[PDB]
Image (tube, rainbow over all chains, first blue to last red; front, side):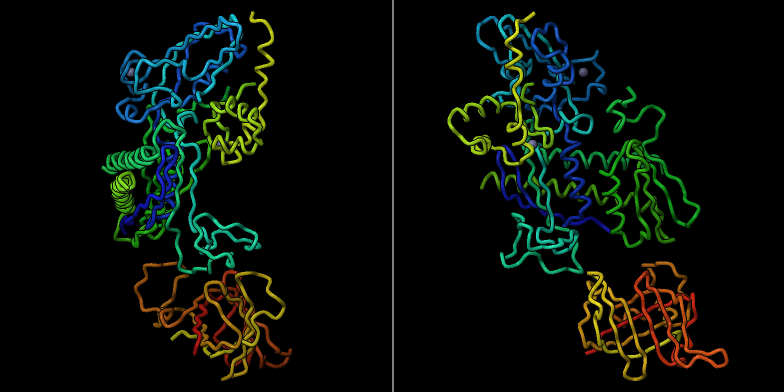
Length: 254
Length: 115
Length: 65
Length: 148
Ligand SMILES: [Zn+2]
Ligand SMILES: [Zn+2]
């Protein structure tokens, strides 16, 4: 009537992704962790844009929407930030937001690429990830783009720009020993990269007592967070959600 | 124009209870937990944890509508064990599990970084 | 119009790869080789660069105001 | 008590018409201590059954080996001594038909009792004397154990 004793084995760790394996766990917990990776890890992304002057071929909403998807290095600064609506400031402050300013005037006879390099933050710890660089817009001669922006804490459930992951590969039972999926012709199906079957075999023998365990993860970071940090913040956030629900339930019972 | 603001899937407007408990009169020792501003993230994991308790006779959850952010969890236990007690025990076990997993994941990262 | 910042499906950054992609095509790469050189494995990401049309170049021919 | 029927059978065909379901097979079985024909749909995936296998079969009104009624509700926390511990494959169904060779003037000598375990169909044909415990729309348990 109690918790499992889950175990971790990291099979690969780079700056782009972490690949690991969780054993001795329910499928629901593993899927919830996989889901929290996408929807509930808070990062910093541009969410307030004031355009002082735009002469580009792209209208203002296009530029703002593109700026929102710029990923920002939010490794440690995100934890000490607060959500803006929770912050008591007069709408903005260094404790709930990070200011950006962009001012690019193409006064030359060559197409000026306005990239992420031109985004200038008021905080050195929160820069564009590429700072090759993400192209915001291209400008002709005599075209100015001048705006300020603010980037705030949020998570991917609200909007996909706060999604830190760039694809979360998730798997379990690579040889289909549980027959949670039924191949009409198992011969035709290529082996998973985690399969332990020899090539003369196409499918592990059926396991009547099996249960899903040994879930294989490959979490790729878009760049806002290191993948280690993505997984750790995900587990911390899910634990925080469960503890808050525990507090509310204790209040409701009392 | 009828698009809801995106924040009304995890934020409680004023006068809204996060979680509400209602006795189920059809069967003895049965309760319905209606949790607002939650989804399958907590519903599925809590249901799976509750199913591991031997004293839980029934544990299920539903989202009554994908555009409405309620989850209803029905829990029925044996008649010596309140469903509320089972629910609290399930959450405590999940929290202990996730804390253990955090610790082991930090250790695994340190070992992989060191070599 | 212009290259999207993110792949629509997986959310991988693909906006900083258009210029490099074109550069690799001027290096006489096959388009598969160029996409591999830029580290785009999932065909969701490969679809982005492989099917993008950079219409903004045509729009910068017209005078500003 | 509460055992409506008991025998030992041997399988003479696993599926004579070719399998129509990948997990369920239609065993055709014969009884050696009597003359009872059995047709039985078995979930072979969890309980594989080979041709020529022998097994004890028991058709019971209840499981608690006291005559106490079962209530027809799943109680995993049941503590009573159950007959299911003595067997490998236990299904629970409802007899839905009892055919016979009765004429308009005589009683049936041969009876054929049909039981449906959630859809898995069983026919048990044989002498009427062995099948008097059956009665249509009565819940019943099929317990089964393969013998060496
Ligand atoms: Zn503030
Ligand atoms: Zn992609």
